[PDB]
Amino acid sequence: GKLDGKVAVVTGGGRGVGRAICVAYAEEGADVVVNYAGNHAAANEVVAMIEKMGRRAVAVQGRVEIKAEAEKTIQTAVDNFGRIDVLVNNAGATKPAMLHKMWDAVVNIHLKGPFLCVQAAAKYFMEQNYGKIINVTSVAGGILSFTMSAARELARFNVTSNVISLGIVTTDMLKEIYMRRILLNRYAEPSEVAPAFVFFGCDDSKYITGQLLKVDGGYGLT
């Protein structure tokens, strides 16, 4: 498994793309912390699917824009599994505000949770001399600049910091990039987006940091 021996924290992991990431990570050998803000029952369903595979997972409640709750979420990984290898800042990436026509003041409120989670994980990445950060956003001083800042400051601890921009309509789920696909009935399953998170979360990307992958089906090519 690409993630054998690794511990991953996925914020907003109970549904949708977050749930697909947790399942894909467990499939690749990870121990998984399923963070949720509200839907405990959905996060427990992910934990149950992962345990049925023969892997390990725990759910944790936290709104990670609140600093103590970001720390709690990171600490749950260390307390249950001893370390935190991968942090996936998924929570909030495809909120309705993230999909509508307008924008630079919407991306700076969604930037506080990723900032606090990285800040809390950094202590452990430094002790481990290893870490993986994946930020998540949706297509349109913000998330990309923060991705590269962390990449530069944590490189010497063997931490990579990358970002995935989601730009397709997933089946679990008014900007023209999504109107086009809805009228054309072209949907992606969340499971089809998870491999990019496995890539940026395992040693396939050891030498790839500060970079963006746009999961948008080529839409920007028009």
Image (cartoon, rainbow, N blue to C red):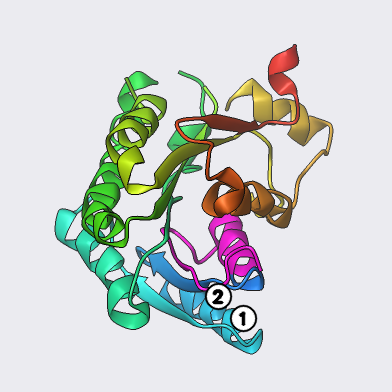
Q: Start and end of the magenta stretch?
A: 1-25
Say whether residue 192 is left or right of residue 60: right
Quadrant where the N terminus sits is bottom right
User: Hey, which quadrant is residue 190 in on the image?
Assistant: bottom right
> Residue 50: where, in percent of width, then height?
59, 80
* Left or right placement of residue 159 versus residue 14 in this view: left
Indicate yes or no whether the magenta region holds residue 51: no
Tell me the quarter of the image containing the C terminus.
top right
| Residue at 50%, 67% in the rendered image | 14
Residue tagged 1? 49
- Image-based side of 93 in relation to 65, left or right: right
Q: For mark 2, what is the residue?
A: 46
Q: Which mark is residue 87?
A: none
Rendering coords of residue 209 (x, y %): 47, 35
Is 187 or 196 nearer to us in this picture?
A: 196
Q: Residue at x 51, y 42 (%)?
A: 94
Reply above or below: 105 against 201: above
Please state which amino acid type lies under the numbered disc 1: Met
Helix, strand or loop for disc 1: helix
Q: Are marks 2 and 1 in contact (CB under 8 Å)?
A: yes
Where in the figure is residue 139, as x and y percent of width and height? 55, 27
